[PDB]
Amino acid sequence: TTRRDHARVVSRSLTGEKFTREQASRDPDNYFNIRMLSCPAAEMVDGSEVLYLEQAFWRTPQKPFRQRLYMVKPCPKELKCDVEVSSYAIRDAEEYKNFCDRPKDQRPLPEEVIGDIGEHLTTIHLNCCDRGKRCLYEGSTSPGGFPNSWNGASYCTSDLAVLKNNEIHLWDRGFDENRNQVWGPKEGPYEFKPA
Amino acid sequence: STTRRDHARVVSRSLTGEKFTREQASRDPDNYFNIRMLSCPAAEMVDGSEVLYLEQAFWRTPQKPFRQRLYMVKPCPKELKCDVEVSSYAIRDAEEYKNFCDRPKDQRPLPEEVIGDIGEHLTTIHLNCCDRGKRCLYEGSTSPGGFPNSWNGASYCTSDLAVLKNNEIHLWDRGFDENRNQVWGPKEGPYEFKPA
């Protein structure tokens, strides 16, 4: 097991169809039932896999409220992490709506997916969890950045936990210039489990 | 002989009070949730502006508002060619003002600190009197191009506000990315707030 083995498990864990329905019925005050549908979209020459990931309210699965292109690749050996997960905005999101259930001929091809990658939103450095912990891999967006690199604008924070049987715990939060949470769940991560 | 200040006080009175989208959510649960809106006068300014505190909460968690605003309702300046000007502002420390409208005036931030705790100017809407036979009393949008916003990958935000009779409020807040994909807010239409 090296970092590309880890990345392949992380990449497989992130794809598929998932629901937060167990968490939604457990705690309806704080969590909704969200459907996550993820599929591989392109392979980089470096070996990095580009996955399409989208999230929708369970009652409107063809109207996703979040659409992303994820890049999962093994961490460089000089970087002290196992797997790197990066999410990107999509230049036009509507050509990509429900990308996972449309045949390859009538959806963006691997040729175009590299060009449709928009602004970089998150980078998460995952590490193998300790012995006995429930997770397989866990990590967050870096608590710190380069000095004077924050432009004073909105910033998002993302925590990611990969568990057994392709269970994904995702906590995407957004903040304003005065550090007040504005979007994303307040209590904790959404727990996505295979249908 | 009804002035612009008259229309602003009409708009102000219809914005205050406790409101819910529960009929719209019961009608269309696929696309709309039951959201509680509680608004009350926050401060009255010397130029004649009315400052309202307005929060929005998921009906299951009314004590955890997901959106807290300070709304300024005033008549449009004479050069602008509109009836009422409504502008929304972020709040300095949102948790300071958490559920501000049920706390009595002694134990909530005073009008002086309220205008002092005003944050970044988010939206500005120019409402106009609707014609007879229309369902609104006042309606307006953010002028094209919207206003800057940075949430979820957005680059700007739009807001549509319609004041209906008997303090019914239609509010549509949306965020769009740089390439004009909607990135937050409802996609199908405005939230319909009816008084409790």
Image (spheres, coloured by chain):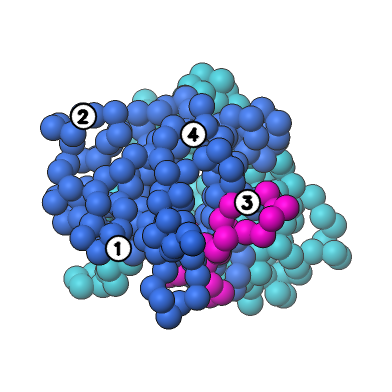
Chain colours: A cyan, B blue
Q: Residue B106: x and y, percent?
A: 13, 32
Callout 4 amino acid: Lys
Any magenta on residue B130?
Answer: yes
In terms of sequence position, does the residue under pointer 2 or pointer 4 come before the other?
4
Q: Quadrant of residue A146?
A: bottom left
Q: Quadrant of residue A41?
A: bottom right
The chain letter under disc 1 is B
Q: Nearer the viewer, mark 3 or mark 2?
A: 3
Q: Which mark is residue A141?
A: none
Q: Which residues are magenta?
A: B127-152
Q: Are marks 3 and 2 in contact (CB under 8 Å)?
A: no
Residue that mark 1 sits on: B120
Callout 1 amino acid: Glu
Q: Residue B126: x and y, percent?
A: 49, 66
Q: Residue A63: x and y, percent?
A: 70, 49
Callout 3 amino acid: Cys
Q: Which mark is residue B19?
A: 4
- Secondary structure under the numbered disc 2 in the rendered image: loop
Whole-angstrom CA distance, mark 1 to mark 4, is 25 Å
The chain letter under disc 2 is B
Residue occupying the point 27% across, 36% down: B100
Any magenta on residue B143?
Answer: yes
Label 1 neighbour load within 10 Å: few <14, some 14-19, many 20+:
few
Residue that mark 3 sits on: B136
3 and 2 marks on the same chain? yes
In terms of sequence position, does the residue under pointer 3 or pointer 1 come before the other?
1
In terms of sequence position, does the residue under pointer 1 or pointer 4 come before the other?
4
Who is closer to the viewer here, A169 or B62?
B62
Whole-angstrom CA distance, mark 2 to mark 4, is 20 Å
